[PDB]
Amino acid sequence: VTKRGLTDPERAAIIAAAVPDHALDTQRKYHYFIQPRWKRLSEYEQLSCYAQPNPDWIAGGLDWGDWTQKFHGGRPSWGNESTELRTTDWYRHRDPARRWHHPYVKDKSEEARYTQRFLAAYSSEGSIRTIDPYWRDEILNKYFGALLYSEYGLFNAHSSVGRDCLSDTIRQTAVFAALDKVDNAQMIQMERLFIAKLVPGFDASTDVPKKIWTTDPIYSGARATVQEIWQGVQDWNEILWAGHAVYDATFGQFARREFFQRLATVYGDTLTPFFTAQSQTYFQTTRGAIDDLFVYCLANDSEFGAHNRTFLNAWTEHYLASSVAALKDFVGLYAKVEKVAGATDRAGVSEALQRVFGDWKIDYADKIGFRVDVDQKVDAVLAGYKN
Amino acid sequence: AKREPIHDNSIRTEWEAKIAKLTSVDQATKFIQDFRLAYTSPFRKSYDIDVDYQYIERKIEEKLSVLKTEKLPVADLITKATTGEDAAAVEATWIAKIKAAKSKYEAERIHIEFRQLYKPPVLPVNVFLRTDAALGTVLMEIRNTDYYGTPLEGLRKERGVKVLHLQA
Amino acid sequence: DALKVNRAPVGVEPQEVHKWLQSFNWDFKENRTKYPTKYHMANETKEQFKVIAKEYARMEAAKDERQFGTLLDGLTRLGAGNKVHPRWGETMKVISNFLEVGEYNAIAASAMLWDSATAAEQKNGYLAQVLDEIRHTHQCAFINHYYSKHYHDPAGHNDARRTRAIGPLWKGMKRVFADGFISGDAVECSVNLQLVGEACFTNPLIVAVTEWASANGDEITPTVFLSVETDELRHMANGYQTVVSIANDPASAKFLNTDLNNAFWTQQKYFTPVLGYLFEYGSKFKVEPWVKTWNRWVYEDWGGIWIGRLGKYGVESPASLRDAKRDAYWAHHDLALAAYAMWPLGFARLALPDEEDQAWFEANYPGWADHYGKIFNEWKKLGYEDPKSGFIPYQWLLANGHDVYIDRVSQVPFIPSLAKGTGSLRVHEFNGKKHSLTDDWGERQWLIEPERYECHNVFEQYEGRELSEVIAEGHGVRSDGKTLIAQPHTRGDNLWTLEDIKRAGCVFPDPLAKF
Ligand SMILES: [Fe+3]
Ligand SMILES: [Fe+3]
């Protein structure tokens, strides 16, 4: 056994004599100088803030000098050229959920283990027996399946964000947002794999869902938007804003919450709400952090707020049109479902769209000063509802 | 001689004085291009403000970018350089330049110059980044070919250094 | 139907989902990496660990609970945070924070690789590493956070994210663990981070860090880094799969061994001497000479086994491996010279080797006593430890012709007149600026790639400024605003203040002015 200075008599005695009998400083708050966002400095801020070694020529950095090694041609390791937006301090952002690595994996681990206990019990229960077979096989398996490709594409839009973004707390928000999105895609496939074990002849292959995502008119608008947000741009603020605040908060919320979660509770589906419960929980956690970055930090920056709102409004104008057209394409799926008054008729879809756009106006548009006529957007999408 | 403090000194202060006088996008574009040509990269014209130019650059960037959002129509933020050139035309010009470069010495100067001239806010960030990545791909392919083929003695003459001391 | 269904209890295990992951990606013309690169990662590359988001979290959360139990429950009850030998407790201020920036930048490097891959499984392997490097960033933070709470000197444990900026030792760390991870071809960054930093250096790093820490009474660091090791095994597999993913691209045969040679030299140039120095000089009890640890893991295990199996995908052993082996014997002793000589620019309290330490050094590095030993003893005699002495050994070096230079590429300090390591001074003037390079490999990097290597060094930033003014500006003081964080001894009394530094009158020169 190796000798250890904690338990070895000789070394423990030598160490005890060497340790002075008083503290050499009374400041025990790790990184005491971080400006606290709330009443007391949090463990989240201590462990995360100023881990990024930015110099003084990237707003907020504490270091100095050029980077030691840059790209061929001179691109800096991190640089102001990475985004159009400007701020007085890139370190200002705070996740309101205060997630460093440990609480983040602690929570998802709870969901991980509880999910499998749930499934073992749901299969034991036989509760799948009451699902509407048409919903299960023609709508849920195919089009909820195809929706994983939206979540997956949104996940991958974060790869350049994780590389490019300019502060530590922002980097944590983006990476957790990315994992939550690929989680959504993996959970959709987990549900289909699960049903295939309970329903003979139910095909859980991704073939048909991918065929739908890549070629079916219902998803061509969404796919075009996702492809642009992911591979069309590199401004990492543009990606975050377009991804979470416009596209996912309108199309993705309507698809997940207003279509698959809501209509599951109209067609006897006791299973899908367990899975959409998780994606919608992740959506609201992600929204709190996106909101802080773009509203509290950037749209209201003391020196660059008007500047940043110019770009945010231009992005929103563009990506909202993309998302409206995505929803116009998508509500053609209603022509495939069994009529349910107040849910799947034109009136029902109208109210669903008023909630999505109405909430979006409150949650996002009004905070950056983006003018939006909710009735106009509802009516634009409703023009795709078949007669 | 004697350096001033790192983060607050007369050189940074004097340049912020010049930057405050900028009142138009054209004027600010000429300013930042002259600045990056004079003080950035190994082919800069002057090292006189070596320890301050990067911070000064940030302040010029912040001024030009605010002038852009205040002065220009929103479409120009997306499609044009602040030179008035169409951003896709600049990308095309410079990608073609570096593809016709005949040596690593030619290509490196095309890539460096593209950045001195068009670094945001001059060029839109999305166009600029994908042009920089395309140029960098070409520069690396030519630099990293037969990378150990030239002895250090020969590399020094090619680079054009003045050798001041070789130990031992 | 509605009455009969199979009611056996079933779930869906991670690998059942994972087998469909590759099919989550789809084809479109713009589905291509955004970063500059000479290589193309193959569309069908698999990964080794069949992990999904939920399984990743479960895996890591279980590790956390064990680790944090030990730290916050058991070790606190033992008072173990103040049962660390002061030399080592000081060394962990530097070791943990320097390693933290390598964890942090590895988040961004892994994201960049995620962007370069086209296969969904390969993106997923890099993503798992993205998350792990966040965990490791916060683990390194937690070491210094915990020391800040429980150890007798929290200064410097409690503010390195700004006090590291004062000194030259941090510049070299930024090259190997920050910029070297994220600036270049993603494949070049992969060999820096994964094939070398992780597959070559992370095993000897962890073994040594935990063995040196426990030898010196530190049970905080083994609790964390033995948990970090379990994650880092997966990252070495990412480095392996990067080489596999590009093996059939013809650009691999043209370029890969150039990127690997450059990356290996990059990493070893600082990682070798800085860890060797921090281990052997920041310790009271000695474990095994750093050189032996380097030989076994770097030269034999990685350069032999790892590199050997990688020949299946065209990898050769780095040409700079011989030069690096000679460095591994003396380069950390060379570095110790500069680190002790410029102690006021650091954020840790240092201890000159005592008589037992010197016997150990001379017995395992024969030649140490007549050279470094004589120097250290002369400095002690001149008042190294005494705040009334007005003596700081950097000025002794200048007075005696032992000038200190900074490699424009690696930022590693170099003292040619005293170095027993590899290396030699080259001083060039280019376009009105003078540059000091210190070895054949870095000089080649600078001559071919001058615009990648424009880092200002401490003599250029501080030229002609007085040392105490630099320290005060950089916040290099304790909470009383006058006593230095850094110290030339580890005793509780006679600590140096800004005024004791000012007495010495150390003013920074331009080391290249004479050339
Ligand atoms: Fe790590
Ligand atoms: Fe790692």
Image (tube, grey):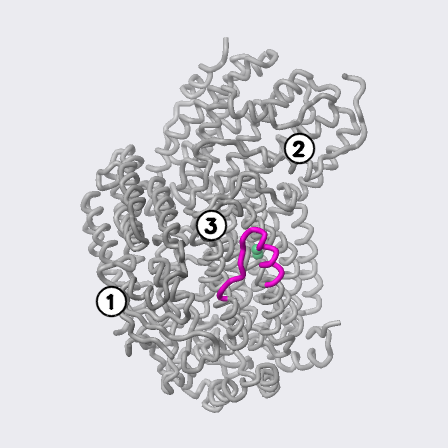
Q: Please tell me whether mark 3 sits on a helix, a strand or a loop.
A: helix
At x 59% / y 73%, what residue is drawn?
A: C290
Q: Quadrant of residue A77?
A: bottom left
What is the chain identity of the residue bearing mark 2?
Answer: A
Query: What residue is shown with label 3?
Result: C186
Q: Amino acid at mark 2?
A: Met
Let me know if residue A305 appears in the view: no
Distance from disc 1 to disc 2, alpha carbons, whole Å, reads 64 Å
- Is A358 left or right of B22, judged from the image as shown? right
At x 56% / y 37%, what residue is drawn?
A: A181
Q: Which residues are magenta?
A: C304-320
What is the chain identity of the residue bearing mark 1?
Answer: C
Closer mark to the observer between disc 1 and disc 2: 1
| Residue A238 image label | none
Query: What residue is shown with label 1?
Result: C432
Q: Quadrant of residue B1?
A: bottom left
Query: What residue is shown with label 2?
Result: A190
Distance from disc 2 to disc 3, alpha carbons, whole Å, reads 33 Å
| Residue density around tag 2, few if under 14, some if 14–19, many if 20 or more, within 10 Å | many
